[PDB]
Image: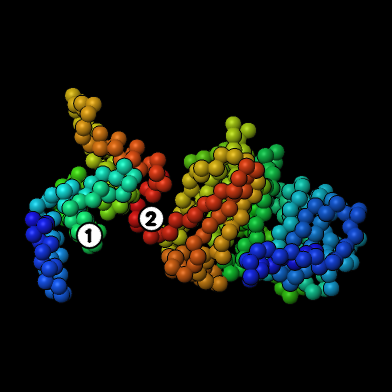
Amino acid sequence: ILGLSYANLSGGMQLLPDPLSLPTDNTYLLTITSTDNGRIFLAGKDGCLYEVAYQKINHSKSSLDDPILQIAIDNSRNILYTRSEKGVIQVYDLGQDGQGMSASVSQNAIVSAAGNIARTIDRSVFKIVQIAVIENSESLDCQLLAVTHAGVRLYFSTCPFRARPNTLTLVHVRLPPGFSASSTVEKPSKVHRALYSKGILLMAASENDNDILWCVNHDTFPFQKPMMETQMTAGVDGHSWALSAIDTPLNKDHIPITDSPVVVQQHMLPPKKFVLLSAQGSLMFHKLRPVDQLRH
Amino acid sequence: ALQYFYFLRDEKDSQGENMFLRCVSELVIESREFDMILGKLENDGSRKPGVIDKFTSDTKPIINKVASVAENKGLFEEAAKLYDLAKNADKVLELMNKLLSPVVPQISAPQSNKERLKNMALSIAERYRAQGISANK
């Protein structure tokens, strides 16, 4: 564990070893995540979960699928999510005395969930590319969004309590625009894909001919009642290693009400800039403000 | 005319200065000698200065004023010219697309290979697009 800081004189980067070593020989630590409690949870290629405490000791939460491909934390609700290789999700309630769970969503649950639509979410086809947590601030009800290989977006609601999680339910689903629903435009969709706070979707698609990048941004403005998403192709053509938000999110309020009004915080909020990392280089994307739109 | 109007400043003080400015503004408007008065063609290399620019200053605001007026009259070309000076690149292309767009639909027998709206189209694209293009995709 080391510390990162910025020199105030040079403005250079300072790294100092905070000599803290933790033996984790057997683990083959695949993933690491943290809760802003400062707690760090990591998984080895040893099942689902483990947690580290610096104050070295390792303690398995899940008491001493197959692997845990991804780990995600819902900062707002102190909720942990784990995605396994098989596509099962587990959401543990992070508590002071440990993790409480584990409710799960699986392909079966999803099938029951649709109860009205189905195909892209076929058994054979069904696979999960990525999972993203949704802040309670953005939506009280919706805990998580799942992105499938197909590029379908699944939204699940939940209900926590001080010690008990609730099983997630499938609130809603969105399909990729081939044009419309049967679309294979998003097929296939890589894990690289991620959702930016306030539902901005960056889709990395790897066709079986090449790599394509798409972005969907809800039109907040018309969103001052109806919902509409503006989706367009992006310049990047190379493999897309990872996406990140350089800047805080533009969201205006810390409540579901007026959370999304970009219009209100266009002035105040810093310009949104997005990172696309490719093997070859870093690409920077900039959000277009309403001023720019008017300008066009 | 510009040379004479410029003398007005010789009486140093506000009022006269504005009178000078108004006079120049009045000259540009209705004379419509934009290229001569305001400037011309970028080839990158910003404006090639007009006579007034040599004298200098408030020139951007006059351009917007003239350009908007061009819009009333519908004197397209003048508007495009004015917006180029304004450096409203996006606006230029959009007006431009409109101009080229109509005249495309119609009936045939035209388009010599050397001068007009099409030719104008070629000028702008070559011109702007390579260079740090500010226009919308």
Instruction: Rate crowding at label 1 as few (under 14), some (14 to 19) or many (20 or more) other CA atoms within 10 Å.
Output: few
**Residue A254's disc number:** none
Q: Is residue A21 above or below residue A282?
A: below
Q: CA distance from mark 1 to mark 2?
A: 32 Å
Locate residue A165: give its quadrant: bottom right
Q: The residue under label 1 is which amino acid type?
A: Thr
Where is residue B109? Give x, y as percent.
Answer: 18, 24
Residue A154 can be seen, yes or no: no
Residue B79, position as x, y percentages in the image: 21, 49
Residue B56 image label: 1
Question: Which residue is depicted at the point 23% across and 46% down?
Answer: B40
Say if A250 sits above or below A88 in the image.
below
Which mark, residue A293?
2
Q: Which image quarter is the N terminus of chain A in? A: bottom right
* Chain label for disc 2: A
Residue drawn at x 83%, y 64% as measured from the top left: A51
Whole-percent x, y for residue B4 in the image: 8, 59
Taking depth in this image into account, of A235 and A109 the one nearest to the observer is A235
Query: Residue A169 appears in which quarter of the rendering?
Result: bottom right
At label 2, counting other C-alpha atoms closer than 10 Å, the crowd grade (few under 14, some 14-19, many 20 or more) is: few
